[PDB]
């Protein structure tokens, strides 16, 4: 599901565009020179390969945030976090999970409230496993709907500020109907 | 989900006059406080409030007053969602969510200009709903209901975080939408 997410971001073609050294720099495979260099790329951006671009994406939006560990407990939750993180930021996505796990812990019966720090840590992963163990697959389904509600309200607010296209948010809701 | 079932579930089969000492509301029957009953022109004893007077008061505050009945002429399903939201959070909270979504989905003002997100359903809000439903069709209505559910779910999160909503309610509310 993550592979599909990144394979859709990395189009069939590099699309090398040379923006100002300051304003983004040269970009290929959606990677700016600045981001590439910060991930140890030293070549010309005209010769950046899809593979190293995918490594940068998997690092920033899957492994760095530790969505791969979430996937160990719930492939579906991790996929939603990953898709959320590429559009809004991985820490925004991680905070949504933490917020929901705190409200659904039954006044701290299942586990104590965690920090909503937006980092997937051992306490976040333990809370997710206890939640999934106590509430079972119905729990997992409830959590996914809840995450979708916080994603959609953030797309609303992004669209109000013009950081997201109307068509994009209409299409995202359309994908979630019956 | 329909309006009659929403009110028929709030009004039980039994009045249950409980005489709170004014502070914690009460005298209350059929979920109606004396304060609300008298503010609706009921002058009898609160012990003798009829179910029918109580239904008239609910219909007044949570269906006609907010103009959800006029919404229902355009979309029975959107009106029923607003009515359910309004009884839990306030009808103007519900009405404002509709205005925000109709503004994002107006295609940069192509279908109709941005309306005031004042939380009051006026002739321009109902005109915008009818144009939206005529341009985007039944798929439009389904999309708008998903979007309204996202803003509802995220407001329940906020309410639960402030302790203004029971965790059980919000889990229950997600589960019924699984």
Image: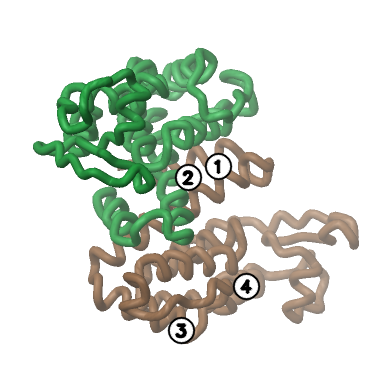
Chain colours: A brown, B green
Q: Residue furthest left?
A: B13
Gap in angstroms between the C-alphas marked 2 and 4: 23 Å
Q: Nearer the viewer, residue A154 or B163?
A: B163
Residue with the mark numbered 1: A168
Q: Nearer the viewer, residue A57 or A150?
A: A150
Q: Are marks 1 and 4 on the same chain?
A: yes
Q: Is residue B72 left or right of residue B126?
A: left
Q: Nearer the viewer, mark 3 or mark 2?
A: 3
Q: Assess disc 1: are there few (<14), some (14-19) or many (≥20) residues with their C-alpha within 10 Å of its C-alpha.
A: few
Q: Assess disc 3: are there few (<14), some (14-19) or many (≥20) residues with their C-alpha within 10 Å of its C-alpha.
A: some
Q: Nearer the viewer, mark 3 or mark 1?
A: 3
Give the quadrant of residue A168. Answer: top right
Q: Are marks 4 and 3 on the same chain?
A: yes
Q: Closer to the N terminus: mark 3 or mark 2?
A: 3
Residue with the mark numbered 2: A172
Q: Tell me what residue is drawn at x 73 percent, y 61 percent.
A: A28
| SS category of the residue bearing label 2 | helix
Residue with the mark numbered 4: A60
Give the quadrant of residue B118. Answer: top right
Gap in angstroms between the C-alphas marked 4 and 3: 21 Å
Which of the image's four quarters has the N terminus of chain A?
A: bottom left
Gap in angstroms between the C-alphas marked 1 and 4: 23 Å
Q: Chain of mark 2?
A: A
Q: Closer to the N terminus: mark 1 or mark 4?
A: 4
Q: Are marks 3 and 2 on the same chain?
A: yes
Gap in angstroms between the C-alphas marked 3 and 1: 34 Å
């Amino acid at each position: 599901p993550k592979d599909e997410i990144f394979d859709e971001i990395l189009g069939k073609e590099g699309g090398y565009v040379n923006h100002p050294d300051d304003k983004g720099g040269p970009t290929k495979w959606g990677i700016t020179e600045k981001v590439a260099r910060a991930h140890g790329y030293r070549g010309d951006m005209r010769n950046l390969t899809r593979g190293q671009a995918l490594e940068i994406l998997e690092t920033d939006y899957w492994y760095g945030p530790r969505f791969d560990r979430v996937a160990k407990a719930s492939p579906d939750v991790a996929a939603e976090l990953c898709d959320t993180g590429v559009n809004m930021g991985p820490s925004v996505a991680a905070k949504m999970l933490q917020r929901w796990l705190n409200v659904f812990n039954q006044g701290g019966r299942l586990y104590p409230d965690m920090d909503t720090d937006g980092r997937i840590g051992p306490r976040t992963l333990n809370a997710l496993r206890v939640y999934l163990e106590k509430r079972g697959k119905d729990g997992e389904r409830v959590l996914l709907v809840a995450l979708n509600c916080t994603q959609g309200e953030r797309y609303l607010e992004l669209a109000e500020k013009r950081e997201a296209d109307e068509s994009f948010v209409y299409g995202w809701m359309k994908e979630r109907v019956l």
